[PDB]
Amino acid sequence: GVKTEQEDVLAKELEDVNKWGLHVFRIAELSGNRPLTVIMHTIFQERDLLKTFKIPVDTLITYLMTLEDHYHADVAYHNNIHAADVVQSTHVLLSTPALEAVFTDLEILAAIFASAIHDVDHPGVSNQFLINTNSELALMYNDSSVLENHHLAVGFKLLQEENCDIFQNLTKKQRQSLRKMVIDIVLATDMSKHMNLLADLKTMVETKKVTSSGVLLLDNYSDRIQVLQNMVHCADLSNPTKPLQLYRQWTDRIMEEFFRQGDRERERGMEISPMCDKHNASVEKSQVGFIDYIVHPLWETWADLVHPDAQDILDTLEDNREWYQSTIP
Ligand SMILES: C=CNC(=O)N1CCc2c(sc(NC(=O)Cc3ccccc3)c2C(=O)OC=C)C1
Ligand SMILES: [Zn+2]
Ligand SMILES: [Zn+2]
Image (tube, rainbow, N blue to C red; front, side):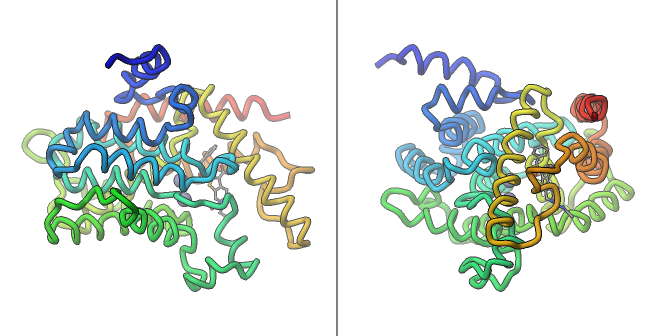
């Protein structure tokens, strides 16, 4: 009834679960490629979600292992490790002082569950690739947020496997509300919705209302869900805000995935997607471009929303951007 030594080392690494920059690749190794399951279980216990939602623990573990198994180990970036990273990052963002006591237990559950499922069964190619290949998925979803609709359908469908229904004790009211928020959050991870999400985030910063305890004031669903959508989108795009040793590992992985799509696009003979061309790419230029145009405007606006809780994260992003720039041949 006592941890093995490997379990002990894993447990000590998980003591950093509340911190930006968790060694998530080490946790994946230590856990035997179960980063999503162990991190989720840890967060659910830490936030007392099992008791609050009457979730039986064997059901939670069974579902988590099932969900984790439906991520593709042969996909370099969009895999269970990425899912675990987004979950843990969302967990840290939810704990930010500016949001203390703002969200209900069910909204917290929605943000974390949405994070866990948000990329499940990702084939490692883009929506546009699936559309252009006449793939079944694209036909199923009428070319519209193809992957994101799929991640949702899979994440929910897996609740129906043996001893997997972690929501079995929620009321119909709780379930309908949970399901709607989860759907709204995952559909918001489609990059084609990025400019719109950011627009609404800026608007909210402009009309920002704090309240009583120095805490953000969100008094309608539209506002509450937009903050959660943006929070998870930030987590999804948090790699360049992490310590450089982590960030670089993620960059390698996504470029591996992109270059592979590029190869398959050359094989087939389609015109090669942006920065997916292995032979004449600039990994460094692309990272600087992606940060200047997407990641920095997003995180800067988030930082404004929760000022100054996110200052250290933004500084790290800026340091990493300078590093990648300095490294341009
Ligand atoms: C015309 C619009 N273009 C886009 O919407 N995309 C093109 C590039 C890109 C993503 S998502 C994503 N990256 C992420 O989603 C998270 C991440 C950021 C930085 C390093 C590793 C991973 C990238 C990217 O990194 O590009 C640079 C190589 C989607
Ligand atoms: Zn995604
Ligand atoms: Zn993702």
